[PDB]
Length: 121
Length: 121
Image (cartoon, rainbow over all chains, first blue to last red; front, side):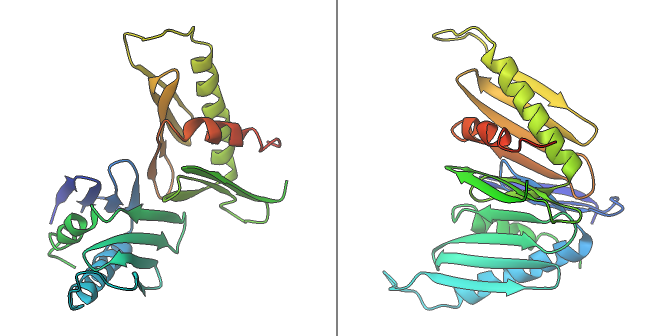
């Protein structure tokens, strides 16, 4: 898997095999942050894990509580917050230059789908 | 100047003297990125430079062209785009983990004012 930039309404996911240290990229339309291979692997794994936990929640016309689920590794921390049919995703990187990121509910499903298009790792 | 976090509607600016490598912070309400001292010094200087160029433009009820001005150093690149009374600010860091950032026009004046409250450098 060579050099792909994916993008949509409010999100970006990129990968460059040739990059010596920072081959990954995640972002909204307006912000973006570079990631190491280890972090991009973790980003996908944990984003997909959270999405799947949430999708496994039985549906409800109007749930009483907002959901707040988190998954983390040594390299990053992720949090879903909102409702099963509309939740935000927050990211905080642990290493080197730290960055805090956030995707509105509107953008999340396309981003999650985008992470499956990195079929290596 | 010790440990200050400033924040307002759509922006954050922070400084921690005690931090060994990344004492600076700039962000919107939802995204944030850490900066080295050299980069925070550059961020302020260049943001204030752009703001002042723009404020020195004679006013017009409805200008024919959108403005696009940039200032850069070895460490970062900044760009104002829009109109003198309402312009966006974009940032791209050059070193280490690179980050692309952007502040909507609404947030810019308070952020610019915030950079003057780092009266050392």
